[PDB]
Amino acid sequence: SMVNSFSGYLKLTDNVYIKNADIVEEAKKVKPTVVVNAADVYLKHGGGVAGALNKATNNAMQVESDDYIATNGPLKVGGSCVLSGHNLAKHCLHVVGPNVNKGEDIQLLKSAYENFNQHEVLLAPLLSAGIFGADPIHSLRVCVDTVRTNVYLAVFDKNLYDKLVSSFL
Ligand SMILES: Nc1ncnc2c1ncn2[C@@H]1O[C@H](COP(=O)(O)OP(=O)(O)OC[C@H]2O[C@H](O)[C@H](O)[C@@H]2O)[C@@H](O)[C@H]1O
Image 1 (cartoon, rainbow, N blue to C red):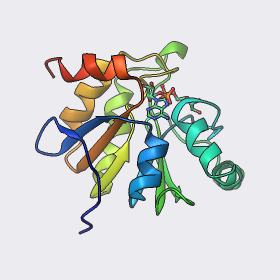
Image 2: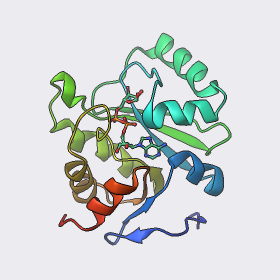
Image 3: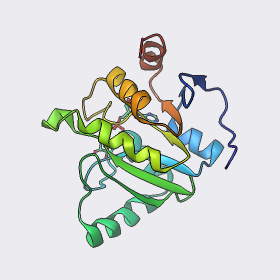
Image 4: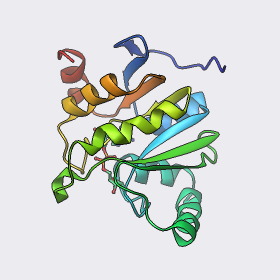
């Protein structure tokens, strides 16, 4: 059931682990079965996790995503799709957290994290915690209280990581 080479993760719960790391570098090191992208409904991979993952695939993720949207239309807020992980992972699970900065319901963050339960092991970011404007501690708490499968969270920002791991969740 895949034993992966995740290294240097702090344990949060039975099934959630966390590390101060760039998700791109973790994916290159581990080559997991599933890397999660913090996507938008249009799969336009501009910045943050999505832009960094896409750049590391030499834009192949974006080209594949454009074909996905042309065939299927936008994802739902809280929804997901499974696409290739290209050189980074077997699969990329593109998951859309709510864009709280655009008035989308923060409750949809739970629906977003539920997608993780369809996969035994994931390398993932904190959904909605960047430009989508959700409180990062809240995103972590929802993750812990929603995901039952094994999730390795990569937190790029050191100061944020230090705050998250010293917080009650
Ligand atoms: N390379 C990285 N590795 C790990 N964590 C990262 C990295 N880059 C950012 N983070 C953290 O990952 C967390 C999420 O930040 P975000 O990636 O903005 O995702 P969202 O769900 O809020 O916004 C999605 C939009 O952003 C994109 O443009 C998409 O195309 C969408 O339009 C934050 O804590 C970041 O510090």
